Image 1: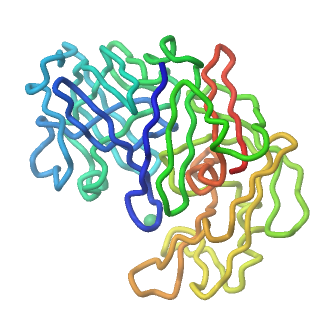
Image 2: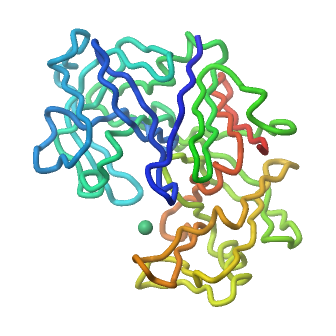
Amino acid sequence: STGSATTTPIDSLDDAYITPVQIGTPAQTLNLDFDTGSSDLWVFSSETTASEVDGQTIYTPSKSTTAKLLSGATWSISYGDGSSSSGDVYTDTVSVGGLTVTGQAVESAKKVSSSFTEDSTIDGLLGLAFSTLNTVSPTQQKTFFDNAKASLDSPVFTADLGYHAPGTYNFGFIDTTAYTGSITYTAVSTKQGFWEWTSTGYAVGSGTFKSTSIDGIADTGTTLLYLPATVVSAYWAQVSGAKSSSSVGGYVFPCSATLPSFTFGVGSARIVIPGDYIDFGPISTGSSSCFGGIQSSAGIGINIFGDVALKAAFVVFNGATTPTLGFASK
Ligand code: NA
């Protein structure tokens, strides 16, 4: 089997991407944030505290003929941005892009933090990291990918995120028309439960490539590119008037600037992030200070290749017995 679903930016900055997901019988379609940096599939629901729901579409298990309470199971998760959610668990039928899993754990939110309530466009998350990070207790649950895997034509999914445009998540096949050149595969460590890999270095603009190992994760649920402070300072030093602002919470730059590209290494291959991808616009409405898309990872404890980096590539998440990542230009 295979599945193919379009993923759409939630706003004009590509802050996140939503993908429609069918849950239950008859189908209830919710727009989920597919997150390769977490392992829970959780949704706004008929159980979510009413004051914490503001425009989201909810899952109502009582209206699904295939829903069953997973008795005694609870979940609670905290993300890198300080947001959180928690609740109870149902099993139900879940379909993505025509690929169906029966008996998927659907984690129903009783509580969500303010950042979730305030984002009316995101109805929940669908985690695609390794199932060792799933928060369900006392019986840990599998991701949608892990449950689908054995049915898939190939044990893979691909992320093809757009810049200011829709893109695609495919399950079970490589679309050889969706990229240019060849795919370069690189080793993955699953020790921390993430799609963790080592980039071979970077360049700023037309500058020379610096060969240096950068361990980090491929995370579709993170908007920005978080890298070591040395790398990030080297980038922003090429932008006149750029500075790190403790008041704003990262590097800002004059909105009048033209940003340089950023290149990262994948083995002997190179992925180029155009400068435009690194502009996240005014810090507040009407400001002439713009927020940068490359930020320091210092204090986060891991480097994160988030959407700024991933949307410059066709990315293969190879879930074979020995997992690997693949990157191609597009
Ligand atoms: Na922000």
